[PDB]
Structures are given as structure tokens and as C-alpha cells.
Amino acid sequence: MFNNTVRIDDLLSPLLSLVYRTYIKGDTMTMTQGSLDHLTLCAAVDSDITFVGNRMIAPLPEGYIPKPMHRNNSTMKMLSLYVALKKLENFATNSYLMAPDTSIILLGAEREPAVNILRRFNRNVSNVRIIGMGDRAVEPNIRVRVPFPIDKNISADFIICDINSYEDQSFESMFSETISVVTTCASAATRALVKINHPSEYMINSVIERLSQLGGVFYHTALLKTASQNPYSYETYIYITPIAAAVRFPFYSNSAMINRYMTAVADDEMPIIPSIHTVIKGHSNTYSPGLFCGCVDVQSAPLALSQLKSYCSEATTWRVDSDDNLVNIIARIDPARIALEFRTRSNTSAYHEYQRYVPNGLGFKVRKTREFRYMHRE
Amino acid sequence: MWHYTSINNDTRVALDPKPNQIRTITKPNTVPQLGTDYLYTFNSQRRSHTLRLLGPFQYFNFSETDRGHPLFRLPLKYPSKAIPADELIDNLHSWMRSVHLLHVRSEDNTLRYNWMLGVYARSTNYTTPVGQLVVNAPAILNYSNPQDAFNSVFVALGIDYIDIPITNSNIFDDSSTPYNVRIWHAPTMTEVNHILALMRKSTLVSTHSSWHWNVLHTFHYRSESDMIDHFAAKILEDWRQKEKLDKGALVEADRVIQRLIPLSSSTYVQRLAAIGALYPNEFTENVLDLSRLSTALLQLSDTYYQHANDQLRRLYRRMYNDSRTLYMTQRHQELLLAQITADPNILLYPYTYIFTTIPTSMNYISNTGQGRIKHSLTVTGATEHDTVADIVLGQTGEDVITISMVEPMSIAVEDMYGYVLDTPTRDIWPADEQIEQKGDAVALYDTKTSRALGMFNNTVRIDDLLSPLLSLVYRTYIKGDTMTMTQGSLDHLTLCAAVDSDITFVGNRMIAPLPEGYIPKPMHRNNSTMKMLSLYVALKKLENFATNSYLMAPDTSIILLGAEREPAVNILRRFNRNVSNVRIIGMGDRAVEPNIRVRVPFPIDKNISADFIICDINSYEDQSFESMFSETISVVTTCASAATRALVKINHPSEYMINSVIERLSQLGGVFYHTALLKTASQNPYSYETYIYITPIAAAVRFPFYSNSAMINRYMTAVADDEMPIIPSIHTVIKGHSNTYSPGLFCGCVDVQSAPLALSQLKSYCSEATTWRVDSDDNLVNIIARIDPARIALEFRTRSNTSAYHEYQRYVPNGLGFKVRKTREFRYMHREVTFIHKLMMYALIREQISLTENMTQVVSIGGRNLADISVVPLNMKYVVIDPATRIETLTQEKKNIEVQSRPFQFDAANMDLENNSIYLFIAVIMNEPNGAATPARMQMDKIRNVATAMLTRTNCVAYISFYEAGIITRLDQSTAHKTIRVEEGRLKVANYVPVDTLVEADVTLMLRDIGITHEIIRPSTPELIDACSNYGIRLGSTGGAVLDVFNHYSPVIKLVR
Amino acid sequence: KYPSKAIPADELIDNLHSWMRSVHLLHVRSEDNTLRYNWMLGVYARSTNYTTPVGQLVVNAPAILNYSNPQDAFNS
Amino acid sequence: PVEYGIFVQRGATYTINAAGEFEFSGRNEKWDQALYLSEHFPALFSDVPLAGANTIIAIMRLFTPQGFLRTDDLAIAANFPRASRNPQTYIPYTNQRGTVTNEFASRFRTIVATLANVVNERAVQDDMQKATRSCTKQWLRHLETQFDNIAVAHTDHLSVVYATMSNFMLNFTNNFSGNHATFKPDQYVITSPEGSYKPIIERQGETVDGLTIIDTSIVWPILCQCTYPLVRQSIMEEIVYPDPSTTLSQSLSVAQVLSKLTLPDAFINMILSGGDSVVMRTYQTEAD
Amino acid sequence: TVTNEFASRFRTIVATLANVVNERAVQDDMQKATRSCTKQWLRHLETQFD
Ligand SMILES: Nc1nc2c(ncn2[C@@H]2O[C@H](COP(=O)(O)OP(=O)(O)OP(=O)(O)O)[C@@H](O)[C@H]2O)c(=O)[nH]1
Ligand SMILES: Nc1nc2c(ncn2[C@@H]2O[C@H](COP(=O)(O)OP(=O)(O)OP(=O)(O)O)[C@@H](O)[C@H]2O)c(=O)[nH]1
Ligand SMILES: Nc1nc2c(ncn2[C@@H]2O[C@H](COP(=O)(O)OP(=O)(O)OP(=O)(O)O)[C@@H](O)[C@H]2O)c(=O)[nH]1
Ligand SMILES: C[S@@+](CC[C@H](N)C(=O)[O-])C[C@H]1O[C@@H](n2cnc3c(N)ncnc32)[C@H](O)[C@@H]1O
Ligand SMILES: C[S@@+](CC[C@H](N)C(=O)[O-])C[C@H]1O[C@@H](n2cnc3c(N)ncnc32)[C@H](O)[C@@H]1O
Ligand SMILES: C[S@@+](CC[C@H](N)C(=O)[O-])C[C@H]1O[C@@H](n2cnc3c(N)ncnc32)[C@H](O)[C@@H]1O
Ligand SMILES: [Mg+2]
């Protein structure tokens, strides 16, 4: 419920649309050729961008307002896995452009917008192949099943697998499929960045056992998770790379990325849907998680603040106009305030202070306000 | 994740304002703002304006007085362009001032404002009984309980219902509404049951599963089709919402079943309600096209009406037989129960069935929207084909697919001016070698060189090949978009060659902006223009290799001895305009002004000299070999005498011709001549014509004569062909497993049901196949698929005809391409040089292999993904010994291909060479299995081991490819190597790590020491023509420049027992 | 309208586009992949406003414009 | 001419599809009433926007009905005959009680504003004099005044006469839906399996003493040389509320007459209804 | 045909004629009335011709 309510695409949406909105007005100007801001710009707008010189993008041709670049939920994530690959080849880098005469593959593909944004990000670099290659792949991306056909020749300096069968399936098949996926991903590139939909300790360790089984090439490996992933996804990106030395301590056990998955299990109780309370009982302790929201006559306003104090830790309020007597009130329920206030049956409050507020002292705002059922936190 | 998690809520009620806000809901003081108060947009293609009011105003009936306002006159005022934002804001604002809803504001916090009735009463100008009730008792619009909002007006009017007109969402269209909503006086559930049951007695009505304000409301459509579009929009809504609930994400859904229930309707609506209830997998898969949504739903209901699945058919039929019942999944019903729990007296539709949804395992592929699908067909799959019928491809228009003869080359502008050198090897020229080489040269010249070579050399001209790049540079210069470039840069030269006008920089790295209204014509170039330019760049690169500027030094001169118009003389004169004192002149016998017209040899009287000379002489007249010889000799003689740096052409560069030229320079008194063969990237890709480069040097030149040189062999290996050149066919019939197709490509169209079949059949020949439907409404899929000989040599090894047809039928109908744009396939696609060299290798080794008798098998060690399969005959068993090779035991068993999947062991004790076997070592000897390059001594060592290991076997043949050392000497001096390099003296083909090269002499000496029979062969020109013909490939320019020196310096050792 | 200077590109595109909207060739679309459309006869019948016998034949039986074999396109 | 070309290329007619999408003819045929019963509708009244035929569609917006879709309440309660499964005459104009301004008349105002614009642009393309043009506008606004003046007595008096005649027993058919784009009368026939069907609605062309031809010209006297009992109010004529009994008895006489008009035919046919027959062979599958 | 092609050709002809006679009429500084009348006769000719 959380992983699907809080998708990353809608989560990052205002920022991307903001970058597109500034580029359209011509307000944007300076950025490095390899900078992440350059990538965000490539991901914000459908048009090719070209700098007129160092740190200076071309002004828009008159009357031309290119449409925002189309992004599915996995676009920003693929971008971040790309940035992660560039960061993994060497940590010192600030430029994220690929080296000339090198290539990358995005093995999971449909439209694969990231292949387009990447192709557009590296336009000034000579000789940079970039292709999606899914079984559902549309052009530019080649459409092909994994494992690769014995005839076809595929290789790259980078590979961003995102394979995930939509079909419900038996565990043996999901296992063998993921294993063959990581196998071809490792064989086809020096720097694979494979997805794992079900990163159980058994799955990841089996993958390491499989890389151990391949002849003559020891594989350094690491679990990984980008900021561009959906906040609640337990899906994890294993990172394969050959190293000349044998890898001491190669298997996982009680790893963080894995425990994010395995600790989750079928829940004994139904998920808690956030209620929007309108009745403020005095000292009830019967409120489900969510928030009080509504309106009251301004004479009653000091009273309600004296009563919602039992649950809500802080409460925004406002009259909407000087001539409108009601005060609107929003106040989310803090469990810590409940665990505090209900320790004993006394019901004291600073009501005498709150009655000092009426009528002009408790808010004014003509603008519509937009509270969220799920607020941001560090 | 089975249970639906959703917070149901009456959003329409939430939209109704508190009464106090009604005074200022227009926000009369401040202007409406885009995206908050309204959402204007202009579809320029449709030329249709669309204004959509936001907030409470989204639901707004308009009095005819409101329509008389100028704001509604605007779309008529601007037929063509978007209404200017100032006029839109001003007019919309004034009309916003014009509106004022009746209300009585009150202190109660529980109150709302019946906005629907308020705006409606306003729009009628209060003439309906509802309007009178409102105008006399405005306080009646206020309400605490949402339902009693209407019950008050019903009890007050004595009516059983009111019939509200619906809003059109865009406020600009004034078109008559499809239906109207009828609010009923039914406070209890029982009254609602009665109204529904009566509703089934009367035509064209339908209702929601649950109603807003908790008051029953029924849509009444003015026509059947209006009902159909309504139902379809609602089915889209409920399908999307159920798609979100199925993913389990929390949703703020207005009601659990968003789609409508017919109460009385035509057959077609009952069908819509049935498939709409079914929640068919086809929506989740995007199998339906939504452009004509209702039609898609009708066809879908058709497929369900006689579904292969008995469950789905009986379920659809049951849904059709009792359309008045609202079918819904159990997970919906639990949501409905939660809703009844939260609001015990809520009204919701009573007649409802809780069917169990039927799972379907078939995941159709789909992707609507532009983009052709670029299939990669598998050689084999789960499906077993048996005697498949021939699949005719339909004719396709040029409106959809054009077939250009050659692919224009995409390339960086600098790369055009690259060139390759080939220095002489032989220290001497014995007279017997002279008679032999002259015999080969006369015999070759007397019967003209290969007809297929000529077909290619003339089909793929360099001028049309480089055309898009040059015209692009001209097109950017014309728009003023071009700006910075160095004074001497190759980009400056390309610019001088793109436009007729003189260019002058205003300062360093900054060209002058075009004078206003001036658009100079593109510079005129014949086929030999770019080539002469590249020979000039080659001369500048040969005077010193360090240079980046290509301008001539002041007080120096050049001559272009071949001349007609000689555009290069003009582009050069224009390139060096800022340099003082730079004579540049053409001087042909056909020369036009500026170029002087004069015969070569020069007249005894005339004085000619220069620091550079670019001869391009080529008599058009057919002639005897003695005359061509003496003429070319006198041409090189005067070219050498007249300049310190001649760059003479040779039309027929036989070993005899070039060596005779060197003998002639040797004969001239007192001046030893360093010399080198040369070929630019700007030359025609297939021309064997070569530019010999003369220059005096103070030292006598060791090893001055040529023998078996690359540039020469590019010519002499070509000879009259035994067979007619292979013209690329365009096949339209896909026979099942035929092996009768000539090189070329399948192209055409098929009905989309037949599409998976055709892909299952063209897989036999084509390695990859692009496809696309042209439109959502057009059933045919266009298909282009060129024939790969490697795929033939693979698929026809055995008679089994398996394919992944079951996968391909997942594609239909939306899953295999969409593109409105015309596509332009080429009969001769571009390829990198290394790939073409590989195909020449395969042609050479295959022709070499067909000659051998009684060979049991071909063992290609390091065979990767079956890449050498084109060489091996369909009979003999194939064996791969590359660790990198993927294992496919089904494909292996079905196609007679054993695969070791282990590293080969080159140690002689571990060696296991079978008798009657052909061991391929094509470019595998130079690399370790992990890909790191092996040191050259280790390479010669493992070659020595494969040599000694074969010494015992009665019949065996190894083909050990390797790189000769001499190439590194040549690429140190050359420029045209975008792919090949020389990092720290080692070759660096493609993306492989640099690798040290063997010397041919030490290797042949070593093989003589082994005592094994051997032969160092390399692919010839006819093998190149064979590769390009059979594969449908054109060579390109840089590839044509570097192919000679590269392919000549990748010998294949041919060990034999 | 423009004896002296080139017709401005905006007017050319706009007018040519509106006339392009103005044209609509008679046809009966069909599933067969082997079919073509006798474009010559279609535009010709259109230009006569379907008054020639070819024009009547097309206006009454537009499907006759479709053809598999190119020659039978006219023989029909 | 240009928008006309763009419109007419789409076709002069269309048919609503079984999927409900419009399908325009693509041909410029002259309409005939024989088509009125055909699947086709005139294309002008499709109310479908076209990319460059906007002024046409706009002027066609002026023809939209200003009435409402009243249920035939009393005719239902009286249990009068009704072909429709829910009877519904479309009354041309709403009663306008209490309004300072008449909505019908204001609609006519916006219509004549758009008409003034069209006739104006034609007038300037025709380089015709300022005088004649201003005169055409003067007549347009004079029409608007006459229309306000008359409509005050149209919407508020005649409409209850439509609303009352909607309930008469013999008015069994539905007449309109208000949607010009899609309305077509339900076409019942008396099919006989052993005969050919007789359509009820047919272009039989018999004029019923001239009844089936329509002069649109009649609107001019209505707007101009005719008076209404409400319009006169400054004399106040009392409104007339006619005795129901006349049309009720006339309806009863018609009904009662045709009710027994068919009886002998109906009885005889009832008797012979099983009498139709088919020749049939009977092959014998077994001995004896 | 709904419309006669001969008559439509005469229509385009009289359109061009209206243009020529117009530009002569404006070069001759002649009154708006006489000019509009010439156009009225031109279109009347067009109707008679259809
Ligand atoms: N005139 C008018 N119509 C309304 C108003 N509110 C809702 N409606 C109409 O009521 C019909 C059904 O009401 P809803 O259930 O709230 O709307 P819906 O069926 O979910 O579909 P949408 O209105 O498109 O969102 C819709 O077709 C609306 O056009 C209103 O305030 N005024
Ligand atoms: N529920 C349902 N019944 C159908 C469907 N198609 C045909 N029928 C049944 O078939 C009867 C009439 O058959 P047809 O005349 O062939 O149907 P149609 O209108 O021509 O539609 P198509 O089958 O698409 O050609 C109807 O009374 C239905 O009961 C369908 O798609 N859904
Ligand atoms: N009206 C009309 N004429 C056509 C059409 N197609 C071809 N023609 C005419 O047919 C004549 C001969 O046909 P083609 O052989 O295809 O044309 P061509 O002789 O090679 O010479 P070009 O038409 O100039 O390319 C030409 O003069 C064309 O004008 C058509 O679709 N409509
Ligand atoms: C989660 S989606 C994301 C794809 C891609 N990242 C994008 O831009 O949309 C992964 C896709 O991989 C495809 N796929 C599933 N199994 C595959 C396989 N075995 N080999 C290749 N692709 C596969 C599926 O069709 C699925 O749509
Ligand atoms: C292949 S053309 C190319 C000429 C020049 N590169 C250009 O820009 O067109 C070579 C020309 O040299 C001229 N030519 C032939 N024989 C010659 C000779 N003996 N001396 C001088 N010019 C000669 C021919 O007329 C021929 O047109
Ligand atoms: C040039 S590639 C393939 C050769 C040929 N061009 C082809 O495509 O079939 C050589 C491959 O052989 C493999 N290889 C390298 N050393 C090998 C060895 N000692 N034994 C078997 N295979 C080896 C490497 O993985 C490398 O990818
Ligand atoms: Mg809605």
C-alpha cells in the first residue's frame, strides 16, 4: 500500500516540471557539460540541448516550446543507476558523460525513456552506443529475450538490467530466471548493475555462488539502492564487476538491503488507512491515525484547541476572511502526544490562553491550503 | 495484497462551498489566474479552443444571457491562432464579475451550499419551479445533511423529481448535451428500489452504482449513441480505478464501481456493461485501442461472446442476460461493505452479483504510440512447425516504405580528410619478377576488372555518400547557427567546401555573421572534389604530422594537375584567403578558367613549379597498355620533376606499374626518391585507384620497391568474375524453411493476425526484423527484414523448423509497432570496417573449406556466439570452444552444434586435435579468455603448439588469424583510423584492449622449423564483393580507406596435414 | 497576389493546408494486404466531379478503385 | 467557399454507427426527404467540429432548440395510448415567470449579433455602401425588438398550450428529443410474415389536403403581423381556457371508431393464424 | 453534380475580373457606389450563368 501510494515519479514530479518550466522561459543558463543538472535538464525536455560554449546552453529558437520529456516510473531510477555506474567506475568524477568509444545497455526495455535521455545527454560525445533490449522493447531499443540467443553478439562496458517478469510464477522459475539474467549480465559486461525483485539472502547468495562457478573470473559484488527508486521498494540492484584478486568475504548475511525485504512478511492486521476526524471528543483516546480537519465558530475555537491538544501536537488554524466567522482547523494526530496526555485522567489545558486569540488572533488566509495525508520527514 | 485499500468519499459534496464563500466564490476583486481559476488551451491541429473553469465553477450551467457575453464570442473571433491571454483573462474576468449566485450566509459550521441547484436556478434565470423556490427562499440552498439538500426542494415543490441539464466541460462548445441527469425524491433505500424497478420499464436510462449527495440520480440520454459514449467513458474510468486498486495502492476513489448500470438500453449498451464488468485482461495489457474506445469495447465483447474460455464466455453471457444487475468482484464488495459500515444509511445500488474473476495466463505484449518494433528473431523455440504454407507479403506503397539504394554515411566532419599509407617492402626488383608482374599486369588490364567491383564502385559514389554531411554544414551556416572554428581546422575546410561565398573570421575562432538578406548558394562539387581536398590535407599532413592548421605557408604554391572546373582549386583558394602569396591552380588538358589548360608532359617552353602537386590525370580514352604505361610514367616523371611533394594518381596500380614508376625515379640523376602508396577517406569506397606519394630525401631509400602491398592487392586480386553480380532482391513471399532466397531483403505487409506467423517463418533467413502497424485503425503490419547468410548457415543445418511463435502471438495487435512516418530502408546498409573484414575472412575460409574433401567436422575455438557459422557447410558438425558462448542445449541438439563452453588449452600435451577436422582460430589467438591481450611471444608460442600438435594427425586444417607487425608502422603515419589505433605501439581493434602483433617473417621461419605444411593467405577483393553482396552491405568511406591496409595485415595462417 | 516577391511561407503553408483539407478521394478501405488503390482514376474521377463514365463508376462502386493485380485495375 | 469545401469534403450526410461514432458520407449529394427515414442525417446539424469549417459549425449553432423535454405526465396518468416507452414532447420554449428579461429573446439577441457579423463581413467583401449595410443592421435590431416584444407572450402563453396538447390522447408519438444531431422517429411497421410490411411513417406523398408541405415563411407573420392576448397587455384580454370536452370527445370518437374498425379482419385472421403451412417430406428410417 | 463545373469556372473568372475592374476603379478614384454596383452586376452574371 505504501510502495504503491508513494510512487517516485509523482514524488519527484514538481522538481522536474520546475526545471522544464524554467528552461521554457529561457531563465536557465549556466551548467557544466557533465553535471547532474545537465542530466535533469535532458530528462525535463524532449528537445536536444546543445551548449554554445562551456557552461552556456543555447537560447531557445523563437516560437519553439518543446514538450516535456516523457517519463515512466522507472525513468529517473534508470538514470540514477547510470550515474551510479559512472560513480562506481571512479568516485572522483564530476562529469557523467560516457567515454568516447564505449557503450551501455538498459536490458529492461519498453519505451525505455532513459535510453533516450541518455542518448541526448551524451550527444557531444563521439561513438556512444546506448540501447534498451527487453522482450517488450520498442524502437530504438532492440526487442530480444534474455538469456540472449546463441547467435546474437551482445557486449558493453555497462549494463543496467531492470528485468521483472509480469507473470506470476513458481519460485524455481523466478530463481532460474534471475540467475540466468545475472549470468548473462555478468558475461556481457565488465560492469553490470542487475535488478533483483526478491532479494532474499538465498537469492543474492545463490547469485554469488553462480559468479563463483564461472571459470577464471572472480567477481567483486555489492548490493545497492538509489535515491531515485521508489521509497518503499525492497527491490535491490546487485552490482557485479570482475577483479583480479579473489574476493574475501563474498557472501551476504543479515545485510541491510536484504533485511529491508525479508523482515517484511504477511501482516496480522489490515493496513491503517488515515482517517479525517471531525469530532473532537474530550480526552477520548479513540482516534485512529490520521488528522482532525474542519471548521468551527470562532467563539468555539479556543475550546476546540483546548480539546484537540489531547491528540494533536500542533494545530494550524485560520479564519478565511474578516467577515467569515468560522475558523478552519487542521491538526494531525501525534501518537507521542497521546502516549503523553493519556498517562493520567487529568484534562488540563491552556484554554485561558486560547480564548485570548478570538477573534482576529487565530489566522487569516484567502488562499486554499493543501494538507497532505502523508507529510515529509528527515 | 488481495484486499483493496481505498478511502471512499463524496468528492462532489466536498466541492460544494460553505455559504459564506459564495459571496466571493467568483473572487470578484482579483483576476482569474491560469491553472487555478481556469485551464485554457488551443489545439492548433484541430484548431479548437478549450476553456475549462476550475474549482466549483467546473459545474456550471450558463444562462443564455451568460452566452451573450463577449467571452464566448472569442473562439469565433480567433479561428486560426490561440486567443491571446490578455483577452482571455480580461473577458473571463468580466464574465466572472457578471455571475452572482443567490444565497443566505449563516453562522452554522455544519452547513454547505447546494451549488448545483444554485447555478441551475441562476441559469434558468429562476423560471423553473426550482428557480422560484430558490429566488424566494435562498436559505433553502444551505444544507447540513447532503441528501436533505434536495428533499427540502422536493417536499417544497411536491414534485417526485427534477431534471438538471448536464454541463459541457469545455465552456466554449455550446453543442446540445447528450443526456440530462434526473434527481429523484427517494430518501429511503426502498423508495430508490422502487424508482429503479420503474426505471427498467422505460427507454434510454442508466444510473451510477451509488450517488452523490446520497440522493438517487438517473441519466436520461437523448439518443442511443450518446448513451454508448457515456458508458464507454465510465468503463474507462472504472477500469483505471480498478487497475489502481488491483496494484493495492491507496486511492481516493469517489465510489467503488465507477462505471454505469443500464436500466434500459439497447443491446450494444448491454454489451458494454458486460465487458465493462468483466475487467478483461486486455485493458491491462493495452490490447485495445482507446482512440475509438467504444468500438474497441464492442469488438472485445464480441470476442468474449464466443470466448475460447468457457468460464469467460458463460460469465460474459450471464452479464449480458442480466444487465440491470451490477456485477462486481468480491474485493469490490468488501469495500462497499466498509462504506455501509461508515455511513449506515447510505444509498447504493441494490441489485448486485459477486462473481469470482477468472484468471488468464496470456500476457500480451503492447505499446501504443509511435515507434517501430525492431524484432530479433530466435533461430529456434518451443513451437514445432510442420509444412507451413507460404506467407505472401502484400505490396506496400512508397507512402510507407521507400528503398534507397545506399545508406548515406553518418560521420564526424574531420574523419573525411583521413588517409592511409603503405610503404614499400622489397629491397630489389629482379628481372624475372619484372616479367612475371608485367605478365600479370598486361593480362589483367587487357580484360577489364571485375564487373561486380564496378557495380559497387559506381553504385556507391563518395559524393552522394558524403552529401548529407556537407549539405548539413551548409544548412547550419545559412541559419547563422555555426560560429566557432579554428582558422586552419578541417571544419573550416568543410565550411569552405559547403558554401560558394568567401568566409572571413572577425577574429580568432569567430566567423563573420551573414550580411542581411544574403543566402549564398552551396559550393558546387563533382565526385572528385572532396578527394582532392583530402589529398591536400594529406600533403599538409605529410610535410609534418604535428600540424593542426592546414593553411599553406606564405610564399608557397600548389597545383591540381587534373582539371576541368576543378572546384577544389576554388575551395582551396577560398580556404587560404587570409594567407599572403598562395598560388593555387588546376592545369588539365580539359581545364577551364581559373585553371590553365595544358597537356602533360608540359611543353618544353612553359615553366611550371610548385611546393605541392596533386595529379588526378586519367585519360577517358580506351587505350593499349603500352600507351597507358608510358603516359602514367611521363605523368609521374613531370610530377616529380616539377615539385618537392607530388601526390600522383594511378588508375591501374599493378605491382608492375608502381615498381616501374620507382625504377623511373631511380633512373633520374642525382635525386633519390622516397615514395609511398596512399588512399584517402574521401576516395570512392570501392576504387582501386591509388595515390603514390613522391618526395626527394638526401639518403638513398632502402627497400624502395613494392611487393604484395595492400593498395596494390586491392586492385590485382580483382579480376574478371565467373558469375554475374548479385542484385539485391526484395522478397514478398516467405516460404517455410525454403533456403531459396537470393541476397536482399523481405519487405511488405500482412494482416496482423498473420503477423506472428510470418515472424515465425522469416526467422529462418532474417536475423532481425523491423515491423510496424501504420495506424491504430489500420490492421496491416508492415515488415522489413534483410536476409542474413549467417542465419541461413545456422538455421538450415538440420530439417527441424522450431521457432518462438508462441511469443510472437503475444504481440498482436498493439505489440508489434506503430509509426505514421514513412520509413526509408537501404539496399546497402552501413557497417564498421572490422565487421566487413570479418565477413571477408568468412568468405575466404568458406570458399577454402568447400574445396576440402572428406572432413568430418569444423571446430571453431573461440567461436563466441556462433559467429563463424557462415563458413561451415550445412552437412558437417560444428563445434564451439569459446567460454564466452552461451549454452542452448535445445538449439544445440536441434541444429547439430556441440559447444565445449570451456577455455581452449594451447599447451601441446593437453592438445586434442581430431583427424579430418577444420580448426578455426579466427582472431582468438591474440587474446586471453578474460579479454586481456596476450604478449606476442606467448602468441607465437601457442601458434607453435597448435602447429606441433597437428604434426601427428593424418588430416587436419587450422586457420590461425593474426595481425602482422607492419600495420603498426603504417598507422603511425596514417590518419584515417577512427576505429583502429596504435596505443603504445600495439593494435587496438574496436573496443578490445591493445594487443601486440606478430611479425610475418619470424612466424613463417618458425613454421618452417616445425616442418608443417603452411600457407599465409588473406581475403581478396572478390571476397569483399562477396561479403557486401551476400550481406546487403555497402563499405562506406573510412572503411574503404582503411580496409586495404588492415585486411592485408590480418593474415590467416593455413596449417594443413 | 505576389507578382514580385516570393509568397510568404506562412500563407503558402496555410492555404496549401486548407486546400489539402479540401481534397478527399473516394475509396472503400479493406483488410486485404494485396490491395492497392487506383490513385490515377480516383483523383481523375474527383477532378471531373464524377461526371465522366469513369466518374460514375467510381462514385457508385468506389471499391472498384482497389486492385490486387495492377493491370486489372483498369480492365475492371 | 473555403469552409464549404472543407465541410462538404467530409460529406453532406452521416450515419451514427453501431458503436455510436459518426460516419460522414464523404460525398456532396443533394438531400431528399426519402433519406429522412434512411440511416443518414444532414451534415450541417451533426454539431461535430471540423478543423477549418468553423464558421459553418458556428452558424449551425444558431439553429439549436431553446426548449425542454417535458414528460407527458397527464397522458400517462390518464392511461392514454403512447408509442414511446417514456413519452416526452419537446416544448419549444420554457415559461419565463418573473424575469426582467426573456431568455428566449436574449438568445435571439445573440443570434442576431452573430448574423449581423456574418452579413457584415459579406457586406465588406462585396464592397457595398455603408448606407445599405447600416440599414441591414437596423432591420436586424428591429427584428430583435419585435422578437423581445412578442416572445414575452410566446414562452409564457403558447408553451402551456404545447404542454397541454402534449397530453391529448391521440398524440401518441414522440416528436423530438431536442438533439438535431441524432433524433430520428422510431419507425414501427405492421410486419406480416406472409406478406410485406406496411411502414406507419412513409413518404407516401399523399398530401392530406396539403398538410405535409411546410411554409417557413409563416414565421414572418408570427414575428410581425400577429397579436397575442399577453402581448396586448394596454388592454387586458382574459385568457381562454377551452372546455376539455370537445377534443376529449373527438379523441374518444376517433379511438372508439378505429378500435372496432379492424374487428372482423382481426377475428378471421385469428382463426386462420395457424393455417399457414410448409410442404415437408418425411423419410422413413426403419421398417414398418 | 451538386454544382456545375462550367459555372464554377465562370465563378473564378468573375472573381479575377472583379479584382481587375476593382484595381482600375481605385486607380481612377471613382466612387464606392459605382464600384460596388459593378461588383453587383458581376455576381448577378455569375448567378445567371450558374
Ligand atoms: N448542472 C450541474 N450538473 C452537475 C453538477 N454536479 C454534478 N453534475 C452532473 O452530475 C452528473 C453525475 O454526477 P457525478 O457523479 O458527481 O459526476 P460523474 O458521474 O462522476 O462524472 P463527472 O461529472 O464527469 O465527474 C455528471 O454528469 C455532472 O455533469 C452541478 O453542480 N451542476
Ligand atoms: N452479448 C452479446 N451478444 C451478441 C454479440 N454479438 C452477437 N450477439 C447475439 O447475436 C444476436 C444478433 O447477432 P448479430 O446480428 O450477428 O450481431 P451483430 O449486431 O451483427 O454484431 P456482430 O457480431 O459484431 O456482427 C444478438 O441478439 C445477440 O444476442 C455480442 O458481441 N455480445
Ligand atoms: N492524371 C494523372 N496522370 C498520371 C498519373 N500517373 C501518371 N500519369 C501520367 O502518365 C503519363 C505517363 O505515365 P508514366 O510512365 O508513369 O510517367 P512518365 O512517362 O515516366 O513521365 P513522368 O510522369 O514525368 O514521370 C505521364 O505523362 C503522367 O502525367 C496519375 O495518377 N494521374
Ligand atoms: C519493470 S519493466 C521496466 C522496463 C524498463 N526499465 C522501462 O524503461 O520501462 C521490465 C520489463 O522487462 C521485460 N522482461 C521480462 N522478462 C524478460 C526477460 N526474460 N528477458 C528480457 N526482458 C524481459 C518485461 O516485459 C518488463 O516490461
Ligand atoms: C578524372 S578527371 C578529374 C579532374 C579534376 N580532378 C576535376 O576536378 O575534375 C581527370 C582529367 O584529366 C584530364 N587529362 C587526361 N589526360 C591528360 C593529360 N595527358 N595531361 C593533362 N590532363 C589530362 C582529362 O581530361 C580528365 O578529365
Ligand atoms: C575475436 S572474438 C571471436 C572470434 C571471431 N571474430 C568470432 O566472432 O567468432 C575471440 C573470443 O574468443 C574467446 N577466447 C579468448 N581466448 C580464448 C581461448 N584461449 N580459448 C577459447 N576461447 C578464447 C574470447 O572470449 C573472445 O571473445
Ligand atoms: Mg465524475
Image (tube, coloured by chain):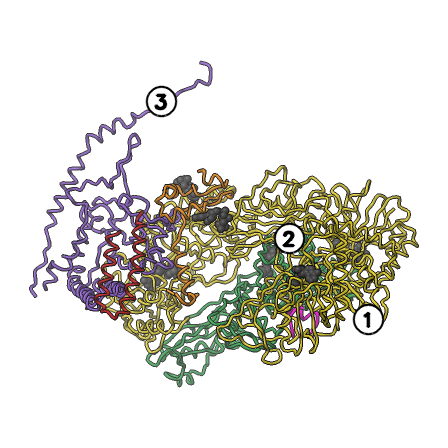
Please determine whether, in this image, residue B257 is positioned above or below residue B538: above
- Subunit under mark 3: D
Q: Which residue is mark 3?
A: D279
Q: Position of residue B1016 (x, y in %)?
A: 83, 53
Label pair 3/2, CB-CB below 8 angstroms: no
Q: Colour of chain C?
A: orange
Which chain has been coloured yellow in this picture?
B
Q: Position of residue B449 (x, y in %)?
A: 72, 50
Disc 1 is placed on an element classified as loop
Front position among marks 1 and 3: 1
Tags 3 and 2 both on a single chain: no
Please determine whether, in this image, residue B656 is positioned above or below residue B749: below
- Quadrant of the picture in which ligand 4 is shown: bottom right
Residues drawn in magenta = A81-98
Q: Residue at x 56, y 66 (%)?
A: B522
Q: Residue at x 50, y 61 (%)?
A: B5
Which chain has been coloured red in this picture?
E
Which chain has been coloured purple in this picture?
D
Q: Is residue B1038 left or right of residue B225?
A: right
**Disc ID at residue B664:** none
Name the amino acid type tagged 1. Answer: Ile
Q: Colour of chain A?
A: green
Disc 2 is placed on an element classified as loop
- Subunit under mark 1: B
Residue A90 shown in magenta: yes
Dot 2: within a 10 Å radius of its alpha carbon, few (fewer than 14), some, or many (20 or more) residues? Answer: some
Tags 1 and 3 both on a single chain: no
Q: In the depicted view, which residue is nearer to us: A3 or B951?
A: B951
Q: Which residue is mark 2?
A: A145
